[PDB]
Length: 184
Image 1 (cartoon, rainbow, N blue to C red):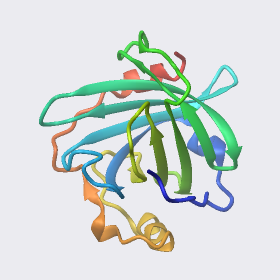
Image 2: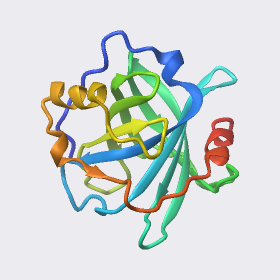
Image 3: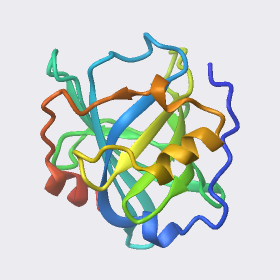
């Protein structure tokens, strides 16, 4: 189960974050480890498509090769805090698992600037019991975390030394598919 009410960034700039471009996860913190594998790759695109707030997700396990994409419609709870359904799709947006009640995640942008961000997410999926996940994002898949986002980690009363990096997994991303999935 999740335990955190993450606080959104003061003065969060939604149009800058949701500008249609890709964000790479560079570092993550799972509060119930063994939720996820230690070695992992993830990225998303975030934007408005025909008036609708959307995210597209990509997950890849670099050892098992498990791979999946998702498309989500985001509903606003408050500035910087969203509830997102998800549908599992192939890379072209063809539906594999339809949207359903109880399959959703919350998404809070705790810090963002033009190049980096800190988010919290609470995933709900059927029967599963999942805990809080934090992620450090960058526009550059290889960027070491800078002082602005590391300070935000500290201000959230978290220790960046606890986060696991994704940078040594040889992850390669199809950014074109993530961008096109925003419309699907």
